[PDB]
Amino acid sequence: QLREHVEPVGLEGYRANKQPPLPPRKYFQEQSRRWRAKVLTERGVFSADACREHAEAIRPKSYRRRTGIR
RNA sequence: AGUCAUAGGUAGCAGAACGUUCUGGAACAAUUACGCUGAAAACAGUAACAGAAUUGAAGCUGCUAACAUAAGUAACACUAAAUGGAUAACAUGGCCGUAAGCCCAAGGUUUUGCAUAACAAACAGUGAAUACGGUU
Ligand SMILES: [Mg+2]
Ligand SMILES: [Mg+2]
Ligand SMILES: [Mg+2]
Ligand SMILES: [Mg+2]
Ligand SMILES: [Mg+2]
Ligand SMILES: [Mg+2]
Ligand SMILES: [Mg+2]
Image 1 (cartoon, rainbow, N blue to C red):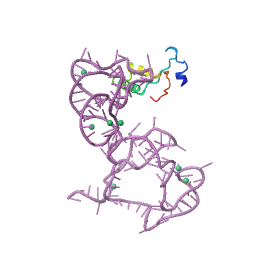
Image 2: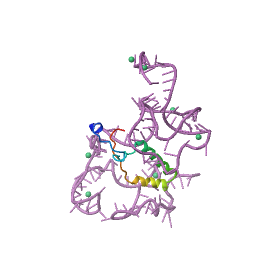
Image 3: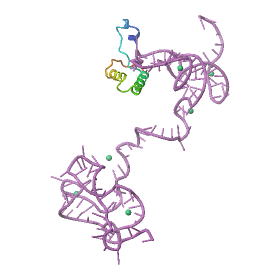
Image 4: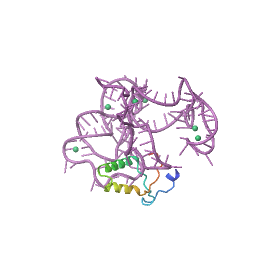
């Protein structure tokens, strides 16, 4: 609590002290899943969208950990 | 934008809104979204204005589907009996023997034969010639 409010720790810029993003929330995961199902249905497996989405899925991602319940 | 007044509720009555699908206003997601939070709630984060509704579900011993629990529990006790490193051909022992043997009928309709795994059902098999049963 003192680290949050009393000592001066969050006083630098944004480019310093920035964090990796939190992982995508479940609504956005469901939206992306629906988009991928749409793409594989009406555009095909061998499309640029499907292959690019798979290629972006295979690469690792730098994330944080959720601390709260939301 | 400063003072006051009111705000427990079942049945019931009244008012304001959220969300789902579709349509009109030319087209509001081709190449996605993803700072993770905001809001009093229903919720929001891919328009808005109107309209048409098979428009909102823990709650009907409701229906359908999937998955648990009981639980690796109960069961695998009607019988003759098995043994040799094999559901053995060989050897030993046992059981039925008015049957648990043999020949047919009704019914079934290929359930019938072949490979020391295998690639095998995709392959075979039912012969009227004794005055056999039927058909008359
Ligand atoms: Mg009241
Ligand atoms: Mg009161
Ligand atoms: Mg339109
Ligand atoms: Mg209805
Ligand atoms: Mg056992
Ligand atoms: Mg034996
Ligand atoms: Mg017969």
